Image 1 (cartoon, rainbow over the protein chains, first blue to last red):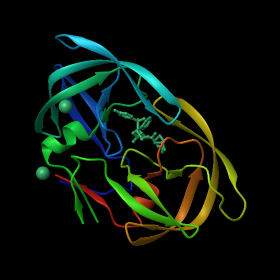
Image 2: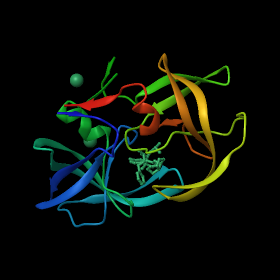
Image 3: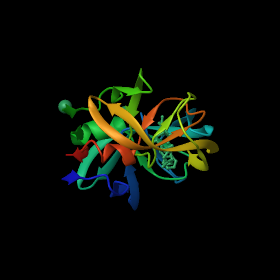
Length: 99
Length: 99
Ligand SMILES: CC(C)CN(C[C@@H](O)[C@H](Cc1ccccc1)NC(=O)O[C@H]1CO[C@H]2OCC[C@H]21)S(=O)(=O)c1ccc(N)cc1
Ligand SMILES: [Cl-]
Ligand SMILES: [Cl-]
């Protein structure tokens, strides 16, 4: 796909068996999803942005299907106002910014 | 250019005669720059990111160079942790997301 940026670049993802909407976010180092359960071990992290920091759970080796493309990597879970797909998984689906 | 996302997509911007670095951010509706002086009047705006809301100063029709492309549009000024180029100016330079 080629996604213009007139609107928020939202896509459908599948994570933990669940279908969700998420923002493709080149400004995010890592993927951050709204509170949900995921399997396996986790450890706490703080992530910061405009407005300050939030505490998240870091889960490693999580598979997400993004717009029909499979990716694996770290997923942070916590009180983000929006589900964000960050660069750690955008790279795996071969996403680029072109102009 | 085609910019991959293994590293942060940082580019040089030029505003007010000054070079700065900024993050190309498809997850930002708005362009938000760290405190600096800009000409003209400003209007209030609140923007909401990961850890909460902040007040910023909204300046309209500001001339800004982004990775060597000219844009003229809205620039928000406030305590952002990094200079961010949002969709309002990414559309002006013709950026798309591709995968
Ligand atoms: C601010 C950047 C350095 C980092 N942010 C990614 C960014 O794209 C967020 C992502 C975002 C999007 C919506 C709500 C919260 C956060 N957008 C954002 O704060 O944009 C603000 C300016 O334009 C506005 O439109 C969106 C909110 C405003 S972040 O959400 O704080 C973030 C930080 C660390 C990680 N791992 C993941 C995400
Ligand atoms: Cl990862
Ligand atoms: Cl690559």
